[PDB]
Image (tube, rainbow, N blue to C red):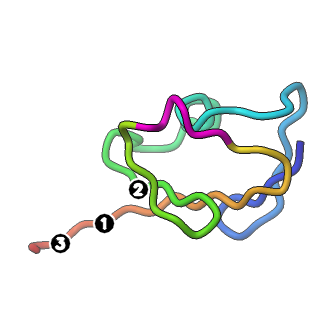
């Protein structure tokens, strides 16, 4: 399947879809504990990572927020 990750082309052979939890682990996203995930321009809630699914053509973004506020 094809998807966009942080604005760039990405491919996942062997899967037609994946939930966010599997995605984070597979891509072994650093400090996944405190990383923010955006799917198709919407910030996701960590509580729904197991249910939220990424399919061919979706755009995912990994962001990290740090600061005193």
Q: Is residue 42 located in the magenta-colored stretch of the structure? A: no
Question: In the rendered view, does 14 fall on the left or right side of 36?
Answer: right
Q: Quadrant of the C terminus?
A: bottom left
Q: Nearer the viewer, residue 49 or 66?
A: 49
Q: Residue at x 60, y 28 (%)?
A: 22
Question: In the rendered view, does 43 fall on the left or right side of 9?
Answer: left
Instruction: Kindly identify which residue carries mark 3.
Output: 67
Which residues fall within the magenta stretch?
48-53
Q: Choose the circle earlier in sequence order: 2 or 1.
A: 2
Secondary structure beneath dot 2 equals strand
Query: Few, some or many C-alpha atoms within 10 Å of disc 3 (few <14, some 14-19, many ≥20)?
Result: few
Secondary structure beneath dot 1 equals loop
Q: Position of residue 11 (x, y in %)?
A: 85, 46
Instruction: Kindly identify which residue carries mark 1.
Output: 65
Instruction: Kindly identify which residue carries mark 2.
Output: 36
Q: Is residue 21 above or below residue 4?
A: above
Q: Report, in whole angstroms, how far the alpha carbon at label 3 lies from the one at label 2.
A: 14 Å
Q: Quadrant of the N terminus?
A: top right
Q: Nearer the viewer, residue 47 or 12?
A: 47
Q: Residue at x 70, y 32 (%)?
A: 18
Q: Are marks 3 and 1 in contact (CB under 8 Å)?
A: yes
Q: Are marks 3 and 2 in contact (CB under 8 Å)?
A: no
* Closer to the eye: label 2 or 1: 2
Secondary structure beneath dot 3 equals loop
- Name the magenta segment's main secondary structure: loop
Q: Are marks 2 and 1 in contact (CB under 8 Å)?
A: yes
């Amino acid at each position: 399947m094809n998807l966009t990750v942080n604005g760039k082309p990405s491919t996942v052979d062997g899967a037609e879809s994946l939930n966010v939890t599997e995605l984070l682990s597979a891509l072994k996203v650093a400090q996944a504990e405190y990383v923010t995930v955006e799917l198709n321009g919407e910030v996701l809630e960590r509580e729904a990572f197991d249910a939220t699914t990424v399919k061919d053509g979706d755009a995912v973004e990994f962001l990290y927020f740090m600061g005193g506020g």
